Length: 121
Length: 121
Ligand SMILES: [Mg+2]
Ligand SMILES: [Mg+2]
Image 1 (cartoon, each protein chain N blue to C red):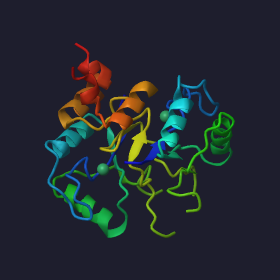
Image 2 (spheres, rainbow over the protein chains, first blue to last red):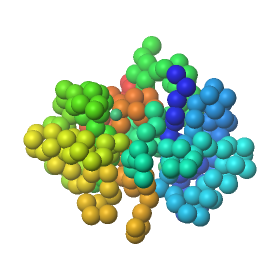
Image 3 (tube, protein in one colour):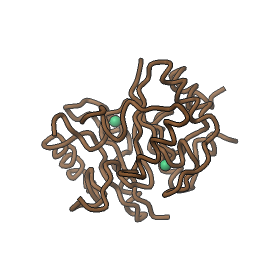
């Protein structure tokens, strides 16, 4: 119901300009904040590590987007470990079939809908 | 062109019966083998670790499905490390919008198509 959502950074929240940071994908940050308002947890899930991760985090922080955690299952993660996050949902531009715009991402999460639902009329 | 594809196990290759292993999702193993024939690399990407991972790997091996690697970027992975795989594609039943059946997964990879393409007529 409330969910832990893994969100990719490059190509997902911003245009893919790695090692640099691209322009924001329209409504990315706002949509994610709306999801937090709805009590979902956001975890940043990026191949970024070290200062390139830090750069992604500060870029988000400056837009008032702060993560439950970054590349961890919880902010002080060994113990009950797995390398892959235990997230309930993955938002990633490299997901097979590609990611739709943030409008549709939001409707899908909110209304519990598949691409199939979205498109079927 | 040839791609490194991360593939989830539970809910993706088999019905989700974790810690047990479910029935195969129709045409999962066959479709993945077809992808290997086309020179893609398959990496198993699962929260499974230890003997539960081993159980997933042997279940696949017994059906003649063998991975480029399991929860690593390459079979002897630190060095150029990131916790998240560097895969080009992710096939995961927890991808936002859900995963379609393996028929459509295959068409999308093969024909370079988005859900948008698939559905637009
Ligand atoms: Mg990306
Ligand atoms: Mg799964």
